[PDB]
Image (cartoon, rainbow, N blue to C red; front, top):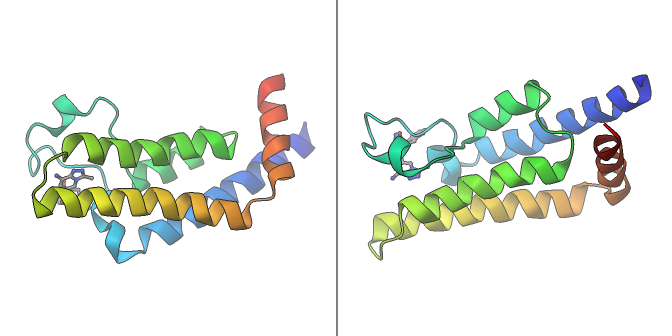
Length: 130
Ligand SMILES: Cc1nnc2c(N)cc(C(=O)N3[C@H]4Cc5ccccc5[C@@H]3CNC4=O)cn12
């Protein structure tokens, strides 16, 4: 229905704003664009589901997220991919892992403070009905 499309449109607006706030954070720069296989050689073969903030925006705009839970699955993927690809004790790997975890924690904290749980419940119920 039109009321349901208004719900998903508000969800997209909310998701774009959260994504923009992550994207402008200096700590999260290396998560703003897809990992370039030319600059990071074995990446696209090791990481099966690459995910980054520009692809998250692309997915919002393509109406791929019908709930905040679906969006957060992709945020979790940015974090888990970095933990998998950079698992060593060296400072380089520890820094990207900390930034990846911080990106995921910031997204969850923004949503905890700003997302009305009845709004998410409505999105979940329209999705489950389709
Ligand atoms: C995410 C992630 N997960 N692992 C690594 C990694 N090992 C390196 C990089 C890394 O530093 N960047 C990547 C992605 C990127 C995107 C925007 C701006 C800079 C960068 C830099 C430069 N080029 C790249 O392809 C990122 N990673």
